[PDB]
Image (spheres, rainbow, N blue to C red):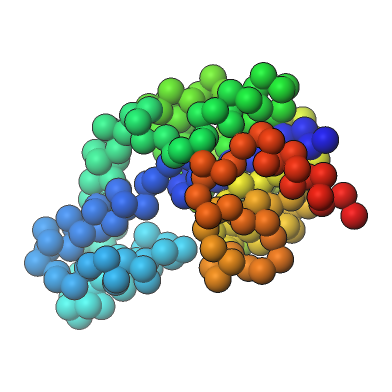
Length: 221
Ligand SMILES: [Mg+2]
């Protein structure tokens, strides 16, 4: 039986993506840049905050000093941090609360493996801190998501090897990160984005202790 479950936050535990989208959109509008719609934002995923801001500036061929550049980047983050102040327990994805309860009562380790610099704050706002045994700190991770580093740090933080874990993800890079760490991935989304070689649930309400166990069993080969 697996000894720990490693959680990504966005797309699994809750949604932050919409908040990032709105923040960028507020910055753009603040400096009169138009075109940052739910279409363009799709090109801002898995990209750096610097690269994203640049893409946005390239929309209006807007030039700015390296100074004004860093300040714009900071503004986007401040908007984001302001926007997440209202995150609450109601924002927890379906099935997640019960899964955490079930894992805890089954003595299965729980760890956050997220790039979010606001992970601890967000879990406290959703009232989930007490379920987590460890939070892998994004700033201590040398290589981002595609790399297995963070799932490896998250597993070690709870005293297990990744090979004794299951990783829950909503992104292709995340799925790859889990595979390369040696943990068993179970994605949420659709094969077209995630891949055809892993178990996938359409929505998180299907992430139950019973389902995880059956998947872990049917893995033994
Ligand atoms: Mg995610």
